[PDB]
Image 1 (tube, chains in turn blue, purple):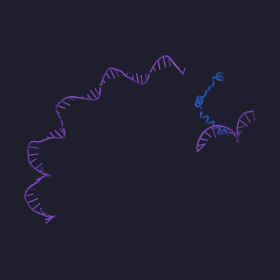
Image 2: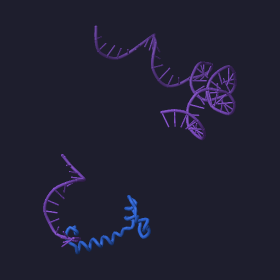
Image 3: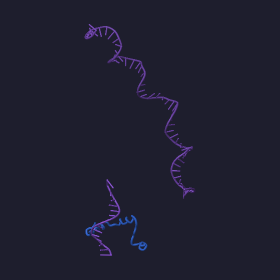
Image 4: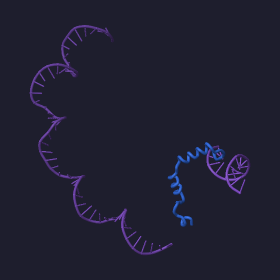
Length: 48
DNA sequence: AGGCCGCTGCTGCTCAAGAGGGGTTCGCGGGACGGCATCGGCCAATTGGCCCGGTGTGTCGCACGATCTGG
């Protein structure tokens, strides 16, 4: 239903192909910086 | 009433059923082709026989004869 209503503006998939597409367009440096900032500031189980 | 800080239970990982149609294989034969393999001659060639013809040098078969040891 959602695809036929608004098929444009996004893409979805199934199986290992979706994970491959995600891993291809993944910014490691930004996520690492976010994790380091949270570690510096955050506390609790979130830090672990 | 949502976010969040712990508890507490639960789970997981590891050490001891036919029928037709068609291209392809191979498998027998099947013989044809070409080839190399096998058998009377054959004469004038190196080695090795097989000797003449000379002596000599050196072993062996026996004669005269001296020395020596045993009999």
